[PDB]
Amino acid sequence: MIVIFVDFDYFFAQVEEVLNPQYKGKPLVVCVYSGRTKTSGAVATANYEARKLGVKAGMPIIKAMQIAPSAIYVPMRKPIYEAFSNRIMNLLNKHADKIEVASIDEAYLDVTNKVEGNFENGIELARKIKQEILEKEKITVTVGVAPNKILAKIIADKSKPNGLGVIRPTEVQDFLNELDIDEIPGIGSVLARRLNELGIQKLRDILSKNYNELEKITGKAKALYLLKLAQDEYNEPIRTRVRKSIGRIVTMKRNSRNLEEIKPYLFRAIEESYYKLDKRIPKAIHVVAVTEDLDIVSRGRTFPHGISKETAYSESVKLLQKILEEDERKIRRIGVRFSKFI
DNA sequence: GGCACTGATCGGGC
DNA sequence: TACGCCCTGATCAGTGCC
Ligand SMILES: Nc1ccn([C@H]2C[C@H](O)[C@@H](COP(=O)(O)OP(=O)(O)OP(=O)(O)O)O2)c(=O)n1
Ligand SMILES: [Ca+2]
Ligand SMILES: [Ca+2]
Ligand SMILES: [Ca+2]
Ligand SMILES: [Ca+2]
Protein backbone atom coordinates (compact mmCIF):
# COMPACT_ATOMS: atom_id res chain seq x y z
CA MET A 1 0.00 0.00 0.00
CA ILE A 2 1.02 3.64 -0.41
CA VAL A 3 0.29 5.84 2.59
CA ILE A 4 0.40 9.63 2.85
CA PHE A 5 0.30 10.86 6.45
CA VAL A 6 -0.42 14.55 7.15
CA ASP A 7 0.29 16.43 10.34
CA PHE A 8 -0.46 20.18 10.75
CA ASP A 9 2.47 22.32 11.99
CA TYR A 10 2.15 23.84 15.52
CA PHE A 11 -1.59 23.65 14.84
CA PHE A 12 -3.43 25.77 17.41
CA ALA A 13 -0.77 28.52 17.33
CA GLN A 14 -0.63 28.40 13.55
CA VAL A 15 -4.38 29.02 13.24
CA GLU A 16 -4.09 31.86 15.67
CA GLU A 17 -1.34 33.18 13.31
CA VAL A 18 -3.66 32.89 10.30
CA LEU A 19 -6.30 34.89 12.18
CA ASN A 20 -3.73 37.44 13.51
CA PRO A 21 -0.77 37.62 11.09
CA GLN A 22 0.95 40.19 13.33
CA TYR A 23 1.72 37.24 15.66
CA LYS A 24 3.75 35.43 12.97
CA GLY A 25 7.54 35.16 13.40
CA LYS A 26 7.37 36.12 17.10
CA PRO A 27 6.92 33.76 20.10
CA LEU A 28 3.24 32.90 20.48
CA VAL A 29 1.77 30.65 23.18
CA VAL A 30 -1.76 29.18 23.20
CA CYS A 31 -2.99 28.91 26.78
CA VAL A 32 -5.79 26.99 28.52
CA TYR A 33 -6.80 29.34 31.34
CA SER A 34 -8.47 27.48 34.22
CA GLY A 35 -9.95 30.61 35.78
CA ARG A 36 -8.71 30.05 39.33
CA THR A 37 -6.35 33.03 39.01
CA LYS A 38 -5.48 35.25 36.06
CA THR A 39 -2.46 33.23 35.00
CA SER A 40 -3.43 29.77 36.22
CA GLY A 41 -3.51 27.24 33.42
CA ALA A 42 -1.46 25.23 30.95
CA VAL A 43 0.13 25.61 27.50
CA ALA A 44 -1.80 23.90 24.69
CA THR A 45 0.90 24.59 22.13
CA ALA A 46 3.55 27.13 21.17
CA ASN A 47 4.86 28.23 17.81
CA TYR A 48 8.47 27.29 17.00
CA GLU A 49 9.82 30.70 18.02
CA ALA A 50 8.47 30.18 21.54
CA ARG A 51 9.72 26.59 21.62
CA LYS A 52 13.22 27.93 21.03
CA LEU A 53 12.79 29.73 24.36
CA GLY A 54 11.88 26.47 26.09
CA VAL A 55 8.09 26.72 25.97
CA LYS A 56 6.48 23.28 25.95
CA ALA A 57 2.93 21.92 25.57
CA GLY A 58 1.58 20.83 28.97
CA MET A 59 3.68 23.32 30.88
CA PRO A 60 2.09 25.70 33.45
CA ILE A 61 1.47 29.18 31.98
CA ILE A 62 3.19 30.79 34.96
CA LYS A 63 6.31 28.70 34.17
CA ALA A 64 6.20 29.59 30.47
CA MET A 65 5.93 33.27 31.36
CA GLN A 66 9.14 32.91 33.37
CA ILE A 67 11.31 31.71 30.50
CA ALA A 68 9.51 33.62 27.76
CA PRO A 69 7.88 36.69 29.37
CA SER A 70 7.77 38.63 26.08
CA ALA A 71 5.88 35.92 24.22
CA ILE A 72 2.33 36.67 23.15
CA TYR A 73 -0.03 34.64 25.36
CA VAL A 74 -3.52 34.01 23.97
CA PRO A 75 -6.50 31.89 25.11
CA MET A 76 -7.32 28.63 23.40
CA ARG A 77 -10.29 28.94 20.99
CA LYS A 78 -10.85 25.26 20.20
CA PRO A 79 -14.00 25.67 18.08
CA ILE A 80 -12.11 27.67 15.44
CA TYR A 81 -9.36 25.04 15.32
CA GLU A 82 -11.98 22.32 14.87
CA ALA A 83 -13.45 24.33 12.01
CA PHE A 84 -10.07 24.66 10.26
CA SER A 85 -9.41 20.99 10.79
CA ASN A 86 -12.78 19.95 9.34
CA ARG A 87 -12.20 22.04 6.22
CA ILE A 88 -8.73 20.56 5.83
CA MET A 89 -9.88 16.92 6.33
CA ASN A 90 -12.48 17.63 3.61
CA LEU A 91 -9.70 18.74 1.22
CA LEU A 92 -7.65 15.58 1.90
CA ASN A 93 -10.63 13.29 1.50
CA LYS A 94 -10.97 14.03 -2.22
CA HIS A 95 -7.32 13.05 -2.75
CA ALA A 96 -7.71 9.55 -1.32
CA ASP A 97 -9.25 6.12 -1.78
CA LYS A 98 -9.63 5.83 1.99
CA ILE A 99 -8.91 8.35 4.75
CA GLU A 100 -8.35 7.85 8.49
CA VAL A 101 -8.82 11.07 10.46
CA ALA A 102 -6.61 10.30 13.47
CA SER A 103 -7.29 13.51 15.37
CA ILE A 104 -8.02 17.24 14.90
CA ASP A 105 -4.41 17.54 13.77
CA GLU A 106 -3.61 14.52 11.59
CA ALA A 107 -4.79 11.97 9.05
CA TYR A 108 -3.65 8.97 7.01
CA LEU A 109 -4.60 8.68 3.36
CA ASP A 110 -4.46 5.43 1.42
CA VAL A 111 -3.65 6.56 -2.09
CA THR A 112 -2.54 3.18 -3.46
CA ASN A 113 -5.12 2.86 -6.24
CA LYS A 114 -5.20 6.62 -6.84
CA VAL A 115 -1.59 6.69 -8.09
CA GLU A 116 -1.70 3.23 -9.71
CA GLY A 117 0.75 1.71 -7.23
CA ASN A 118 3.42 4.09 -8.51
CA PHE A 119 5.24 5.23 -5.37
CA GLU A 120 6.81 8.31 -7.01
CA ASN A 121 3.42 9.66 -8.13
CA GLY A 122 2.55 9.30 -4.47
CA ILE A 123 5.26 11.79 -3.54
CA GLU A 124 3.93 14.17 -6.18
CA LEU A 125 0.40 13.75 -4.87
CA ALA A 126 1.84 14.58 -1.44
CA ARG A 127 3.42 17.75 -2.85
CA LYS A 128 0.15 18.66 -4.55
CA ILE A 129 -1.65 18.06 -1.24
CA LYS A 130 0.64 20.39 0.76
CA GLN A 131 0.37 23.13 -1.81
CA GLU A 132 -3.42 22.97 -1.83
CA ILE A 133 -3.76 23.15 1.98
CA LEU A 134 -1.34 26.10 1.94
CA GLU A 135 -3.16 27.96 -0.86
CA LYS A 136 -6.67 27.38 0.51
CA GLU A 137 -6.19 27.66 4.29
CA LYS A 138 -2.74 29.28 4.70
CA ILE A 139 -1.75 26.32 6.89
CA THR A 140 1.58 24.59 6.60
CA VAL A 141 1.66 20.87 7.23
CA THR A 142 4.30 18.17 7.30
CA VAL A 143 3.74 15.04 5.25
CA GLY A 144 5.19 11.53 5.39
CA VAL A 145 4.95 9.04 2.54
CA ALA A 146 5.68 5.34 3.17
CA PRO A 147 4.39 1.82 2.53
CA ASN A 148 2.61 1.79 5.92
CA LYS A 149 0.99 4.04 8.57
CA ILE A 150 3.75 3.78 11.20
CA LEU A 151 6.64 4.61 8.88
CA ALA A 152 4.58 7.39 7.29
CA LYS A 153 4.19 8.97 10.73
CA ILE A 154 7.81 8.45 11.89
CA ILE A 155 9.38 10.02 8.81
CA ALA A 156 6.86 12.86 9.06
CA ASP A 157 7.93 13.54 12.65
CA LYS A 158 11.59 13.54 11.53
CA SER A 159 10.79 16.08 8.83
CA LYS A 160 9.12 18.79 10.96
CA PRO A 161 8.30 21.51 10.34
CA ASN A 162 6.83 22.12 6.87
CA GLY A 163 8.48 18.87 5.79
CA LEU A 164 7.96 16.14 3.24
CA GLY A 165 9.52 12.89 4.42
CA VAL A 166 9.81 9.79 2.23
CA ILE A 167 10.60 6.10 2.75
CA ARG A 168 10.43 3.97 -0.39
CA PRO A 169 9.78 0.20 -0.28
CA THR A 170 13.45 -0.38 -1.08
CA GLU A 171 14.60 1.55 1.99
CA VAL A 172 12.14 0.14 4.55
CA GLN A 173 14.41 -2.73 5.67
CA ASP A 174 17.37 -0.37 6.00
CA PHE A 175 15.28 2.24 7.87
CA LEU A 176 14.01 -0.33 10.39
CA ASN A 177 17.63 -1.23 11.31
CA GLU A 178 18.72 2.18 12.64
CA LEU A 179 15.41 3.16 14.21
CA ASP A 180 15.81 4.06 17.89
CA ILE A 181 13.25 2.65 20.35
CA ASP A 182 12.27 6.09 21.65
CA GLU A 183 11.26 7.14 18.10
CA ILE A 184 8.51 4.51 17.82
CA PRO A 185 4.96 5.91 18.26
CA GLY A 186 3.21 4.43 21.30
CA ILE A 187 6.40 3.81 23.29
CA GLY A 188 6.59 6.42 26.06
CA SER A 189 9.69 7.83 27.72
CA VAL A 190 9.42 5.48 30.71
CA LEU A 191 9.24 2.25 28.76
CA ALA A 192 11.92 3.42 26.33
CA ARG A 193 14.24 3.88 29.32
CA ARG A 194 13.41 0.48 30.77
CA LEU A 195 14.18 -1.03 27.35
CA ASN A 196 17.39 1.04 27.14
CA GLU A 197 18.49 -0.27 30.55
CA LEU A 198 18.16 -3.80 29.20
CA GLY A 199 20.35 -3.08 26.20
CA ILE A 200 17.53 -2.46 23.76
CA GLN A 201 18.33 0.82 22.03
CA LYS A 202 17.43 0.04 18.43
CA LEU A 203 14.27 -1.57 17.09
CA ARG A 204 16.38 -4.37 15.64
CA ASP A 205 17.47 -5.22 19.21
CA ILE A 206 13.90 -6.49 19.82
CA LEU A 207 14.62 -9.51 17.61
CA SER A 208 17.38 -10.84 19.90
CA LYS A 209 15.55 -10.71 23.24
CA ASN A 210 13.53 -13.69 24.48
CA TYR A 211 9.93 -12.84 23.60
CA ASN A 212 8.53 -14.05 26.92
CA GLU A 213 10.91 -11.78 28.80
CA LEU A 214 9.99 -8.91 26.48
CA GLU A 215 6.29 -9.42 27.25
CA LYS A 216 7.00 -9.00 30.98
CA ILE A 217 8.62 -5.58 30.37
CA THR A 218 6.38 -4.15 27.63
CA GLY A 219 3.10 -6.00 28.13
CA LYS A 220 1.70 -8.35 25.50
CA ALA A 221 0.23 -5.76 23.14
CA LYS A 222 3.41 -3.68 23.05
CA ALA A 223 5.57 -6.77 22.67
CA LEU A 224 3.56 -8.02 19.69
CA TYR A 225 3.59 -4.50 18.26
CA LEU A 226 7.40 -4.08 18.59
CA LEU A 227 8.09 -7.55 17.22
CA LYS A 228 5.83 -7.00 14.21
CA LEU A 229 7.45 -3.63 13.54
CA ALA A 230 10.94 -5.08 13.82
CA GLN A 231 10.08 -7.78 11.29
CA ASP A 232 8.38 -5.34 8.85
CA GLU A 233 5.12 -7.21 9.35
CA TYR A 234 3.17 -4.12 10.39
CA ASN A 235 0.48 -3.49 7.81
CA GLU A 236 -2.63 -2.07 9.52
CA PRO A 237 -5.29 -0.71 7.13
CA ILE A 238 -6.46 2.89 6.87
CA ARG A 239 -9.62 2.80 8.96
CA THR A 240 -12.24 5.14 10.45
CA ARG A 241 -11.84 5.42 14.26
CA VAL A 242 -15.04 5.45 16.35
CA ARG A 243 -15.71 7.82 19.26
CA LYS A 244 -15.87 5.79 22.49
CA SER A 245 -16.18 8.38 25.24
CA ILE A 246 -17.31 11.92 25.81
CA GLY A 247 -16.75 14.04 28.86
CA ARG A 248 -16.12 17.36 30.50
CA ILE A 249 -13.77 18.31 33.34
CA VAL A 250 -13.35 21.71 34.97
CA THR A 251 -11.16 23.41 37.55
CA MET A 252 -12.92 24.71 40.64
CA LYS A 253 -12.26 28.19 42.03
CA ARG A 254 -10.83 26.51 45.12
CA ASN A 255 -9.74 23.07 46.27
CA SER A 256 -12.39 21.29 48.24
CA ARG A 257 -13.82 18.16 49.80
CA ASN A 258 -17.18 19.81 50.45
CA LEU A 259 -19.90 17.93 48.56
CA GLU A 260 -22.16 21.00 48.26
CA GLU A 261 -19.26 23.12 47.02
CA ILE A 262 -18.22 20.54 44.39
CA LYS A 263 -21.73 19.64 43.14
CA PRO A 264 -22.41 22.77 41.03
CA TYR A 265 -19.30 22.08 38.94
CA LEU A 266 -20.07 18.37 38.59
CA PHE A 267 -23.55 19.21 37.34
CA ARG A 268 -22.45 21.85 34.81
CA ALA A 269 -20.00 19.24 33.49
CA ILE A 270 -22.87 16.75 33.02
CA GLU A 271 -25.03 19.40 31.29
CA GLU A 272 -22.20 20.17 28.86
CA SER A 273 -21.39 16.49 28.35
CA TYR A 274 -24.99 15.78 27.44
CA TYR A 275 -24.94 18.59 24.91
CA LYS A 276 -21.88 16.89 23.33
CA LEU A 277 -23.43 13.41 23.42
CA ASP A 278 -26.32 14.75 21.32
CA LYS A 279 -28.18 11.61 20.19
CA ARG A 280 -25.74 9.14 21.75
CA ILE A 281 -27.03 7.40 24.83
CA PRO A 282 -24.33 6.11 27.22
CA LYS A 283 -24.55 3.05 29.54
CA ALA A 284 -21.49 4.01 31.56
CA ILE A 285 -20.63 7.03 33.70
CA HIS A 286 -17.28 7.86 35.35
CA VAL A 287 -16.77 10.71 37.78
CA VAL A 288 -13.17 12.01 37.53
CA ALA A 289 -11.34 13.93 40.24
CA VAL A 290 -7.98 15.69 39.88
CA THR A 291 -6.61 16.00 43.40
CA GLU A 292 -4.58 18.89 44.84
CA ASP A 293 -1.37 17.00 44.02
CA LEU A 294 -2.59 16.54 40.40
CA ASP A 295 -3.14 12.84 40.87
CA ILE A 296 -6.26 11.48 39.10
CA VAL A 297 -8.91 9.52 41.04
CA SER A 298 -11.98 8.02 39.28
CA ARG A 299 -15.12 6.04 40.15
CA GLY A 300 -17.48 4.64 37.55
CA ARG A 301 -20.56 2.48 36.92
CA THR A 302 -21.95 0.66 33.89
CA PHE A 303 -25.75 0.36 33.78
CA PRO A 304 -27.70 -2.42 32.09
CA HIS A 305 -29.46 0.40 30.23
CA GLY A 306 -29.00 3.93 28.89
CA ILE A 307 -28.52 6.80 31.32
CA SER A 308 -30.77 9.84 31.05
CA LYS A 309 -29.41 13.23 32.12
CA GLU A 310 -31.35 13.02 35.37
CA THR A 311 -29.94 9.58 36.21
CA ALA A 312 -26.48 10.97 35.41
CA TYR A 313 -27.02 13.63 38.08
CA SER A 314 -28.06 11.25 40.80
CA GLU A 315 -25.49 8.58 39.98
CA SER A 316 -22.65 11.13 39.68
CA VAL A 317 -23.18 12.25 43.29
CA LYS A 318 -22.96 8.64 44.49
CA LEU A 319 -19.69 8.23 42.59
CA LEU A 320 -18.35 11.53 43.95
CA GLN A 321 -19.22 10.42 47.50
CA LYS A 322 -17.32 7.21 46.75
CA ILE A 323 -14.22 9.22 45.75
CA LEU A 324 -14.38 11.39 48.89
CA GLU A 325 -14.95 8.25 50.99
CA GLU A 326 -11.95 6.38 49.58
CA ASP A 327 -9.53 9.26 49.12
CA GLU A 328 -8.44 11.74 51.72
CA ARG A 329 -7.00 14.46 49.49
CA LYS A 330 -8.59 17.73 48.42
CA ILE A 331 -10.03 17.95 44.92
CA ARG A 332 -8.81 20.54 42.39
CA ARG A 333 -10.72 19.55 39.22
CA ILE A 334 -13.96 17.56 38.89
CA GLY A 335 -15.50 16.03 35.82
CA VAL A 336 -17.48 13.25 34.22
CA ARG A 337 -16.97 10.93 31.27
CA PHE A 338 -19.64 8.90 29.43
CA SER A 339 -19.04 5.77 27.35
CA LYS A 340 -20.54 2.46 26.16
CA PHE A 341 -22.93 4.14 23.74
CA ILE A 342 -26.02 2.24 22.61
C1' DG B 1 -8.42 -22.36 31.17
C1' DG B 2 -10.29 -18.71 28.91
C1' DC B 3 -14.36 -15.81 27.32
C1' DA B 4 -16.81 -11.57 28.31
C1' DC B 5 -16.92 -7.97 30.92
C1' DT B 6 -15.82 -4.64 34.54
C1' DG B 7 -13.63 -0.70 37.19
C1' DA B 8 -9.56 1.66 37.89
C1' DT B 9 -4.89 4.12 36.58
C1' DC B 10 -2.68 7.62 34.13
C1' DG B 11 -0.47 8.67 29.83
C1' DG B 12 0.10 11.90 26.46
C1' DG B 13 -2.07 15.10 22.35
C1' DC B 14 -3.66 9.86 19.21
C1' DT C 1 7.99 25.14 42.24
C1' DA C 2 3.73 26.60 39.82
C1' DC C 3 -0.52 23.17 36.54
C1' DG C 4 -5.90 22.28 31.22
C1' DC C 5 -8.99 19.79 28.89
C1' DC C 6 -9.38 15.93 26.25
C1' DC C 7 -9.96 10.76 25.19
C1' DT C 8 -11.61 9.33 16.93
C1' DG C 9 -7.33 5.76 24.68
C1' DA C 10 -4.04 1.75 26.38
C1' DT C 11 -3.50 -1.24 30.08
C1' DC C 12 -4.65 -4.65 33.21
C1' DA C 13 -6.38 -6.97 37.72
C1' DG C 14 -10.64 -8.75 39.38
C1' DT C 15 -14.97 -11.13 38.63
C1' DG C 16 -18.40 -14.84 37.22
C1' DC C 17 -19.12 -18.40 34.37
C1' DC C 18 -19.08 -23.00 31.80
N1 LIG D 1 -0.35 18.76 25.75
C1 LIG D 1 -1.05 19.08 24.55
C2 LIG D 1 -0.49 18.75 23.33
C3 LIG D 1 -1.18 19.09 22.16
N2 LIG D 1 -2.38 19.71 22.25
C4 LIG D 1 -3.10 20.10 21.02
C5 LIG D 1 -2.55 21.38 20.52
C6 LIG D 1 -1.64 20.99 19.41
O1 LIG D 1 -1.38 22.03 18.50
C7 LIG D 1 -2.40 19.92 18.83
C8 LIG D 1 -1.55 19.05 18.00
O2 LIG D 1 -0.58 18.31 18.67
P1 LIG D 1 0.90 18.11 18.20
O3 LIG D 1 1.55 16.97 18.91
O4 LIG D 1 0.89 17.53 16.88
O5 LIG D 1 1.81 19.38 18.34
P2 LIG D 1 1.73 20.67 17.45
O6 LIG D 1 0.73 20.63 16.38
O7 LIG D 1 1.24 21.83 18.25
O8 LIG D 1 3.18 21.00 16.91
P3 LIG D 1 4.02 20.15 15.89
O9 LIG D 1 3.38 18.91 15.25
O10 LIG D 1 4.43 21.03 14.74
O11 LIG D 1 5.26 19.66 16.56
O12 LIG D 1 -2.86 19.19 20.00
C9 LIG D 1 -2.86 20.03 23.45
O13 LIG D 1 -4.05 20.67 23.52
N3 LIG D 1 -2.24 19.72 24.60
CA1 LIG E 1 0.11 15.40 15.52
CA1 LIG F 1 0.87 18.78 14.57
CA1 LIG G 1 -3.22 7.33 42.36
CA1 LIG H 1 -2.00 7.03 24.83
Image (cartoon, coloured by chain):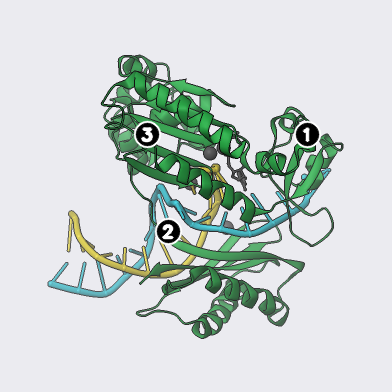
Chain colours: A green, B yellow, C cyan
Q: Is residue A104 above or below residue A152?
A: below
Residue at position x 42%, y 71% in the image: A280
Quick check: marks 1 and 2 in contact, CB under 8 Å?
A: no
Query: Which residue position is annotated with label 1?
Result: A27
Of the pair B6 and A60, the residue shown nearer to us: A60
Q: Number of marks in the image?
A: 3
Type of residue at label 1?
Pro
| Location of mark 2 (residue) | A243
Q: Is residue A259 left or right of residue A116?
A: right
Chain hosting mark 2: A
Residue located beneath label 3 in the image: A149
The disc labelled 2 sits on which kind of residue? Answer: Arg
In which quadrant of the rendered view does residue A203 lie? top left
Q: Nearer the viewer, residue A124 or A276?
A: A124
Looking at the rendering, in which quadrant would you find the N terminus of chain A? top left
* Farthest residue, direction right: A70
Label 1 packing within 10 angstroms: few (<14), some (14-19), many (20+): many
Above or below — where is A284 with respect to A35?
Answer: below
